[PDB]
């Protein structure tokens, strides 16, 4: 009845799995304009189309530092566009412009354009790449979701955002501290469903290593908004429990949406 739902009915185990139910293919990004290249990941099952998410790096870093996300998310039934920025010191707004340029490359020019539903797109990023999501969402309010991982931006006013927003913060992150970055961003968004999850003891580099707590909620957010898949509302609402000895130290959201 929802034509965009993919994969079997989920469970806590299915969303925590390193590999989802979709076999994954991959290839480098070759010939693209408006960003630095990178790597695409996608289901090999071409019986149907899938939503796509672009993922942008941010701490003076390259795609390799986020690459575990490519198979982790593509295997749940998404095309993942993991990009290099034009330069490793690009500012956040240019990174947002590059996220949109990578989505346009993927849907109009990439070898896998035919298995993307160009109407169902999302953007994500770490650090300054996460900071770029304000530009991406406010320049392209048709996006279905944005997901910021330790997002960094001097611009604290994200009230322009009308796209469902998930932020992950790290309790031990001194570079993009929740108090100065993610939480102000989250508090400023008044026109979109939103979700903030803070990982205990996690430093600015938490997104750069396989992290099941981050992955499960990233997957759930993509499913809910990119695929309209209300089978995944159960993991988002109420969402994680919080505590100093738990993986999650803080949790805020607009459940029930």
Image: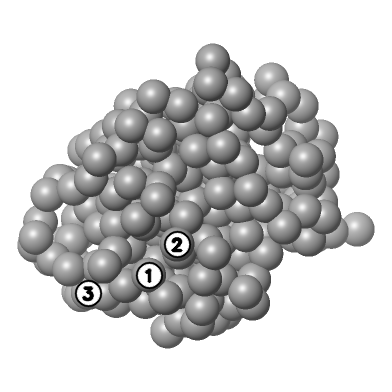
Which badge, 2 or 3, is on the more N-terminal residue?
3
Q: Considering the numbered disc 1 on the image, is that residue within a helix, a strand or a loop? A: loop
For the residues labelled 3 and 1, the Cα–Cα distance comes to: 17 Å
The residue closer to the viewer here, 243 or 20, is 243
Left/right of residue 6 with respect to residue 162 in the rendered view: right
| Residue at the top extreme of this rendering | 245
Is disc 3 surrounded by few (<14), some (14 to 19) or many (20+) residues within 10 Å? some
| Residue at the right extreme of this rendering | 1
Residue ID at (69%, 20%): 13
x, y percent for residue 240: 67, 32
Q: Image quadrant of residue 17?
A: top right
Residue ID at (59%, 33%): 216
What residue did someone put label 2 on?
184
Which badge, 3 or 1, is on the more N-terminal residue?
3
x, y percent for residue 221: 63, 50
What residue did someone put label 3 on?
94
Is 79 drawn above or below residue 10 in the view shown?
Answer: below
Q: Would you say the residues marked 2 and 3 are in contact, meaning their CB atoms lie under 8 Å apart?
A: no
Q: Is residue 199 visible?
A: yes
For the residues labelled 2 and 1, the Cα–Cα distance comes to: 6 Å
Residue ID at (17%, 68%): 91
What residue did someone put label 1 on?
156
Which badge, 2 or 1, is on the more N-terminal residue?
1
Is disc 2 surrounded by few (<14), some (14 to 19) or many (20+) residues within 10 Å? some
Between label 3 and label 1, give the one nearer the viewer. Answer: 1
Q: Considering the numbered disc 2 on the image, is that residue within a helix, a strand or a loop? A: helix
Q: Would you say the residues marked 2 and 1 are in contact, meaning their CB atoms lie under 8 Å apart?
A: yes
């Amino acid at each position: 009845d929802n034509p965009y739902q993919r994969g079997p009915d989920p469970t806590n185990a299915s969303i925590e799995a390193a590999t989802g139910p979709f076999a994954v293919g991959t290839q480098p990004i070759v010939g693209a304009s408006g960003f630095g290249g990178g790597q695409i990941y996608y289901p090999t099952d071409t019986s149907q189309t899938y939503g796509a998410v672009v993922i942008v790096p941010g701490f003076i870093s390259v795609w390799a530092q986020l690459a575990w996300l490519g198979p982790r998310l593509a295997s749940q039934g998404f095309v993942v566009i993991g990009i290099e920025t034009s330069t490793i010191t690009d500012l956040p707004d240019p990174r947002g412009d590059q996220a949109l340029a990578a989505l346009d490359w993927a849907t109009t020019r990439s070898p896998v354009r035919s298995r993307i539903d160009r109407t169902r797109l999302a953007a994500a990023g770490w650090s300054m790449g996460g900071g770029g999501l304000r530009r991406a969402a406010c320049q392209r309010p048709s996006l279905k979701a944005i997901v910021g991982m330790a997002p960094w931006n001097t611009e604290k006013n994200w009230s322009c955002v009308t796209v469902p927003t998930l932020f992950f913060g790290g309790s031990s992150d001194a570079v993009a501290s929740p108090n100065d970055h993610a939480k102000p961003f989250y508090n400023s968004i008044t026109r979109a469903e939103k979700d903030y999850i803070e990982l205990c003891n996690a430093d600015h580099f938490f997104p750069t290593s396989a992290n099941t707590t981050m992955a499960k909620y990233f997957i759930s957010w993509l499913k809910r908004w990119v695929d309209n898949d209300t089978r995944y509302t159960q993991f988002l609402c109420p969402g994680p429990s919080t505590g100093l000895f738990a993986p999650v130290c803080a949790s805020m959201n607009t459940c029930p949406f």
